[PDB]
Length: 294
Image 1 (cartoon, rainbow, N blue to C red):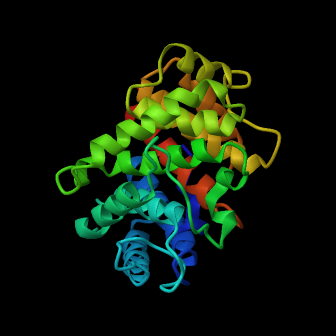
Image 2 (cartoon, rainbow, N blue to C red):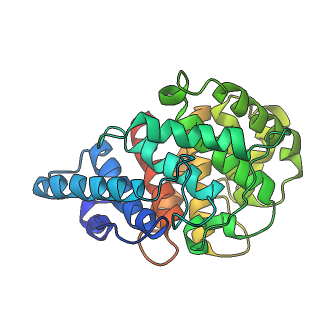
């Protein structure tokens, strides 16, 4: 439970286009989410929350300016829509539903577009127009195991928006099962701890991380406390956060403490260049820990 005093830098005013606006919206949404769940508003300064909610609304409203007729999103209205960005918008908006008024049409419109336009017959989600801001995609920037990493990423967004979009988007359940099929079928082949963690989470969300796959997920953890790859530490923080969420989904509370301890000791408080995924993920994971861990 990172103390509120350390998170002041996360109350960010969003500005910029389709990607930049989201880079700015991210810390504010997750900071409010985290402060709410850990009940730290009094030790943060309750008089700071209303402005934070306004900044979040500011981010949402600004983002809508880049919502294309297809309900997809891109950095600029004339740029081909990005599968990743659209899925990220869904990821953030779904989590901010209780913070501000998110128009279901917008949310579910994006979900629908991803399913009907970017999912292959084998369940794979494909990206036809990569984001300009490659630093905002975290561990996905490493081109290794892209099909798995991206499908897991998009699948996680769809699952978070399932309840809200189920009736409005009938092809949702099928989409989720297909992507899950793809992940399950190739899970034993993954070499990256990042992919093992992100896909492990997507699978656990469906209750499909079992037996050998579950065993691979657990044993991939170095010293039973983190999921890491020989690269940027930021990617490892993000991977370990996805892994923690998977553990909570699995309700494997025995394995959890070492992981949260490692995450805490990183003393990472988000923010900074290329911090979008690590910031959203670490605070989503820790807030979820507060909510679910006995």
